[PDB]
Image (tube, coloured by chain):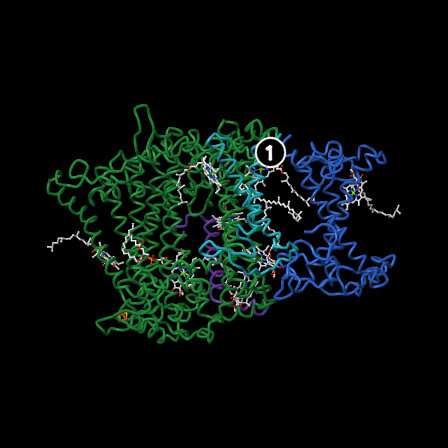
Amino acid sequence: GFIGSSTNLIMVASTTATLAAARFGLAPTVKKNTTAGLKLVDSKNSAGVISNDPAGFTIVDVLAMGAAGHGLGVGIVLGLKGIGAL
Amino acid sequence: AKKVKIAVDRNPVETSFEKWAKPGHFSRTLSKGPNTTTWIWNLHADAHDFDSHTSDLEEISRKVFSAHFGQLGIIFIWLSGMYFHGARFSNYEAWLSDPTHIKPSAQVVWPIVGQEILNGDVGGGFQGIQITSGFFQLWRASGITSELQLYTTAIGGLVMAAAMFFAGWFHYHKAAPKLEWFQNVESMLNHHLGGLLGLGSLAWAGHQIHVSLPVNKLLDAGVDPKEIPLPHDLLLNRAIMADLYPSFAKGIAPFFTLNWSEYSDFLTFKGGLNPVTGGLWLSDTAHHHVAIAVLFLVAGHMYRTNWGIGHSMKEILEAHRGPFTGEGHVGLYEILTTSWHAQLAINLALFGSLSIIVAHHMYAMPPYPYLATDYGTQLSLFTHHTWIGGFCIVGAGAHAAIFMVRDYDPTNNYNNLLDRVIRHRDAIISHLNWVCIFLGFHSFGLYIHNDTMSALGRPQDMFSDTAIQLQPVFAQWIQNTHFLAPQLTAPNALAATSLTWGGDLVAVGGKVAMMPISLGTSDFMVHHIHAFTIHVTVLILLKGVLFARSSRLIPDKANLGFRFPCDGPGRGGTCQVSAWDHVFLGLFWMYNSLSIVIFHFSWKMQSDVWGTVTASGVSHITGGNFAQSANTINGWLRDFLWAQSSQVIQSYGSALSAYGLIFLGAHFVWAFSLMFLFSGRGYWQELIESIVWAHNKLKVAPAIQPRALSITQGRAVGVAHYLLGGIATTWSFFLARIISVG
Amino acid sequence: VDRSKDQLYVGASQSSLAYLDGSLPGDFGFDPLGLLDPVNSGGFIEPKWLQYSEVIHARWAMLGAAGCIAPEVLGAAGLIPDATNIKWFESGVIPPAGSYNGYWADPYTIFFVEIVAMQFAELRRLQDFRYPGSMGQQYFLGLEAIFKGSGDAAYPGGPFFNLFNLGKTEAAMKELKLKEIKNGRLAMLAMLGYGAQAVMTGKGPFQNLVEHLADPVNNNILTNFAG
Amino acid sequence: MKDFTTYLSTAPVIATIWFTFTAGLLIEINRYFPDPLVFS
Ligand code: CLA
Ligand code: CLA
Ligand code: CLA
Ligand code: CLA
Ligand code: CLA
Ligand code: CLA
Ligand SMILES: CC1=C(/C=C/C(C)=C/C=C/C(C)=C/C=C/C=C(C)/C=C/C=C(C)/C=C/C2=C(C)CCCC2(C)C)C(C)(C)CCC1
Ligand code: SF4
């Protein structure tokens, strides 16, 4: 069963972490760009996307962090199999 | 925060033949019509100089965009012709059965004035001109097995050519993008990185995984081409694919479950060359384009367009600011979004350098089946793509100087990297000047040292492997490091990327496909010739760019323009001071430097790599005479030019007799060019006066007054004929030679 | 794209609200790429063509969605002979996937009649977009009386295309147009579902539904990656 | 059409047609009378 396996858990955790990090102001988002000093500052969005989320979390943040989460998860899954851990 | 959006103007221009009947309409000067023959040349010279027809950037951009559709449409006609001639006038089908004995041919001549002798005996019951373009090897790799498949591609090529010409007309006469559209550099890079290169690589991986790999796996096994399954049968029937590659039995579940190791059977990392065909494994090539697809698709999400996330290219440039460089990269973003010439200067430089890198990598890692053992194709492709790279780089200097004269504005450039470079140009050119003199003495002087010592009967005093030695120790170390890479630094690679590093030779059909290349004293000497001739070409072109606007001789050179002959005989003489003349001189040195590169390649391969495998060992075409002979200028004259030109001068009466004719004709055009280079239009204008008098005497004098060519056109006509004659001479000499023996 | 109904969908953006004012049917503010912006529009990317094209796609898709499954449903119920209980992609449209022998003519003979018939239907429809009302002028066997259009290309109306003159009131017509667009958009996704499901599973749309209901967990997109 | 025929009358277009005609005539003559060396 794929569900609950090591591969599935890592991908769900990595995807969840990026969404959680971005939503709670731990990663850059659509409304917060990052300065040269790796600090979050307000940004200007040409196509201001309306969102009812109290923090302004838009659907773009989901796609941005969904792909970022998948990239992180895929690397970990394949990396562990490389060293024999997985 | 200007939004990224589509912006056009409706019906900007009217489609009429009115202006087709009014030559010179584009320019105010030429619109009045001709009075002297100089007008005719000016019409063609300034036709595509859009930046000088109008001062409106938007109008310039729209012409560039549509002129590019015309270039694309022309390539499709050319590509369509190559595929069509393969279907109708080629022996491709016979070649598939016996690739090692049948010479590729895709051109046939009509039987007129006795030219049918050029239809040589190429094999497969076919008569035609042998081709060195390598199209047969490319078609085999992709999986083409019938002339019907070639025919359909040609028809598709013409449809694409029609679409390209429609697009050019549509986007100039019907819906022309506005200037703000052209200036979305962030958006363009995103689409061109992830969309053009990224999806293009992924799409081609799909073809290789589903068409090329199955077809070539059976072809190598010896299956008759007509009995191989058709590509669509492979696509529709997963059962067939499972037989060739069992991984297909599991579908795409491994891809989504991250069990990517399941696909190890067709996504390999072998390295080396396929022993049966002598070319790269297609399974390796598929994993290459899959990896490249992911890298570029990720690369296409870097720049900010409409949704906040991403980078601003202006912000990156302005943040990279150091203590040694004043303001830094400030102002470059405005330069590179308002000057087409500045963009062209960069792109030509790297596009040309890429074409040269292609030449080196394709010969060392032959990517197509039966490409290596076809010595005519290996020599032609390496030489073709080196010449293309050479011309592009010289163009990069030409259009860097055009930017410096026309698009450069001091107000926007104050104490930035560009400004500071101009402020120590004497330091740069003086140092680069000395480096060239140093490299000329210590590389070409060694050849003169060897030639004199050899003529004096003092071989022990020469620079050679049996005498004073100059070993490329640094290059030899790198060859050994790459040879041992699979053991420790690339553990998951089975073999070295190329057989040039070391190991054992691969032989296909009794001929060597690739074997280790040894670097000795001769290789040391020739390489430092390359560094010398390249550094001189940089000196000429860089000098033209840095001194385009002014110098200690002409303080106001910018006002004179980019292309003028001189500023008169004053100050001792100022002939050829314009930046255009630095391109004119740079073309000669580029031709000089690349000629040695392709002579180095031709002699080294025949001497040390190419040859016939036999029981005793490898016998090379020129028998390993490069090491002992290429250390003197006399050796090159006798062993390379005089000995190998035997084939071309004995070509008369055979199918190669055409190369003999072009060999003489090329010699003629080259010498003809020296008439324009060694003379000046002052003599010729006076000569035409006497010739015009004879016509006046007979009431047959023209209404358009004859004029001797301008000063600049004499130099342009001279260099064009000089290059054509020189390059065509080598072209005939190479093909008649390698086809005859290789 | 927010499912169901709502004032605005997920992708609605402040930029798209500039020109999306609810005038068009099914205007839920969803235009993240801003293709319907009137400013500096041209070519085929303009509001009039894009809105017209969506309706045309909607109407073809609705016929396709109902026609690509009816043979399977009717065949499953025994209302048509089993010889015609054929998957939509095995009718003859894609002979490599499957072809049906038994039509009154060869499928290429039938195609020529399709070409000629659609040339008249489609080029006459086009000429009303380029020159509104122009198809009601030149003699066409007296049929030009019903081709006068109504000024809006996508909604010709008239005695035939509005046979039963439904939506007489302005309010009623707006509701009908909204219902047409939503059903049309739903059918466009259904047709894409038929195409994707055919490749992934190789079975008809009706078979996929029946299998899913049997064992929903063991029959879905995730399990069909491998078989 | 007047302008298009004017374009065909330009020097480069006329020369292409004229030499295409002239070359074709010479090629065809040598196709039916191969190897002419003496009037005879
Ligand atoms: C039949 C269609 C048509 C017509 C009537 C016009 C008419 C016009 N165009 Mg348009 N145009 C068309 C198609 C057409 N265009 C297409 C298909 C494109 C896409 C490439 C363009 C792109 C375009 C641009 C970018 C511009 C025009 C311009 C013009 C004006 C002058 C053109 C002129 O003098 O041409 C006479 C020129 C020629 C006959 C040269 C033809 C060149 C083509 C590409 C063939 C190249 C062959 C190649 C060299 C072969 C190798 C040669 C070797 C063997 C020796 C005029 C209003 C100009 C304008 O409005 O300026 C204000 C302008 O700047 N057009
Ligand atoms: C761009 C590249 C590309 C493309 C186009 C394909 C395409 C394909 N691959 Mg390949 N593949 C690729 C890259 C690619 N591959 C790469 C990089 C790898 C390495 C990881 C593989 C590894 C791989 C494996 C291991 C397998 C395939 C398979 C397949 C086939 C079935 C895939 C499937 O189940 O789709 C599922 C569903 C879809 C793709 C969606 C289809 C959507 C349709 C087109 C929508 C149509 C809608 C329209 C409105 C309807 C028509 C209406 C009209 C008639 C009126 C298919 C031909 C499988 C196969 O059969 O191989 C023989 C298979 O087993 N591929
Ligand atoms: C992407 C490539 C590219 C592009 C788009 C351009 C574009 C331009 N260049 Mg640049 N250039 C390039 C590459 C490019 N260049 C390269 C590679 C070089 C190095 C050789 C140069 C060197 C160069 C110079 C020195 C100059 C330009 C100029 C120009 C401008 C006017 C050109 C013109 O009117 O030509 C009109 C075209 C012709 C007159 C036809 C030339 C025909 C050649 C000589 C034929 C050669 C032989 C042939 C290929 C094969 C045999 C033929 C057979 C019949 C015997 C224009 C903006 C000129 C300018 O003023 O810019 C501001 C200018 O002075 N370019
Ligand atoms: C074979 C012909 C030839 C030769 C020998 C040279 C030589 C030179 N050219 Mg020239 N050039 C040539 C053809 C030639 N050119 C042509 C045809 C053109 C027209 C396109 C040009 C255009 C051109 C340009 C535009 C430039 C050069 C440059 C140079 C110099 C390169 C660097 C240097 O100092 O090297 C070292 C010198 C040599 C290799 C010459 C031979 C030295 C001998 C072998 C050893 C010394 C002899 C020894 C002392 C014994 C003497 C005894 C005696 C006194 C009794 C050099 C003086 C570049 C320059 O000036 O760079 C600084 C430069 O910018 N050339
Ligand atoms: C360099 C290529 C290029 C570029 C940058 C543009 C750019 C533009 N074009 Mg032009 N165009 C091009 C080539 C290009 N065109 C060609 C080759 C043609 C002839 C076929 C046209 C015909 C054309 C028309 C008729 C129109 C434009 C329009 C536009 C504008 C909007 C484009 C858009 O949003 O498309 C987004 C794309 C789509 C909506 C269609 C997507 C699907 C297409 C039909 C096929 C794509 C195939 C894909 C690349 C590969 C699939 C692989 C496999 C699955 C088969 C924009 C200024 C429009 C305009 O003026 O707007 C103001 C407009 O009306 N273009
Ligand atoms: C875009 C719409 C569309 C298209 C292109 C198709 C296409 C197809 N359908 Mg499908 N179908 C559709 C929509 C569509 N269908 C819809 C919406 C439904 C649900 C109602 C169905 C239900 C359906 C079934 C149940 C079947 C098909 C079948 C077929 C196939 C055979 C067609 C045939 O024989 O027609 C026959 C032709 C006609 C009905 C038109 C007759 C034209 C003459 C000239 C009219 C003469 C009229 C007369 C003079 C006066 C009126 C008389 C009247 C009052 C009695 C073909 C692949 C069959 C199939 O798959 O077979 C293998 C099949 O069994 N379809
Ligand atoms: C809290 C909340 C909620 C929830 C939410 C959720 C639950 C979400 C989810 C979400 C998700 C869950 C998402 C996801 C996404 C994903 C994505 C977007 C992906 C992507 C991917 C990619 C892009 C990939 C790529 C690749 C490939 C293909 C190959 C290899 C490499 C790589 C990896 C790169 C709601 C709203 C209800 C309500 C309110 C609150
Ligand atoms: S006219 Fe000729 S010789 Fe006199 S300065 Fe000008 S380029 Fe030199």
Residue C133: x %, y % from top left: 77, 65
Across and down, in percent, residue B269 comes to: 45, 33
User: On the image, numbered disc 1 is attached to which residue?
Assistant: B253
Q: Quadrant of residue B495?
A: top left
Front in this rendered view, residue B339 or B152: B339
Residue A44, percent from left and from top: 55, 61
Classify mark 1: residues with Cα within 10 Å, few (<14), some (14-19) or many (20+): some
Q: Nearer the viewer, residue B26 or B23?
A: B26
Give coordinates of residue B134: x percent, y percent: 44, 41
Residue B261 as seen in the image, left or right of residue B600: right
Chain painted in purple in the figure: D
Residue B451 vs residue B190, the one in the foreground: B190
Where A86 falls versus C49 (above or below)? above
Q: Secondary structure at mark 1?
A: helix
Instruction: Please give left or right for residue B306 compared with residue C224 in the image.
Output: left
- The residue shown at (25%, 57%) is B432
**Quadrant, the N terminus of chain B:** bottom right
Image quarter of the C terminus of chain B: top left
Residue furthest out toward the top: B615
Query: Is residue B120 at all visible to an observer of this figure?
Result: yes
Question: Which shade is chain B?
Answer: green
Picture residue at 28% right of the left edge, 63% below the top: B425
What is the drawing colour of chain A? cyan
Which quarter holds ligand 4?
Answer: bottom left
Q: Is residue B121 visible?
A: no
Number of marks in the image? 1
- The colour with which the image depicts chain C is blue
Q: Amino acid at mark 1?
A: Ala
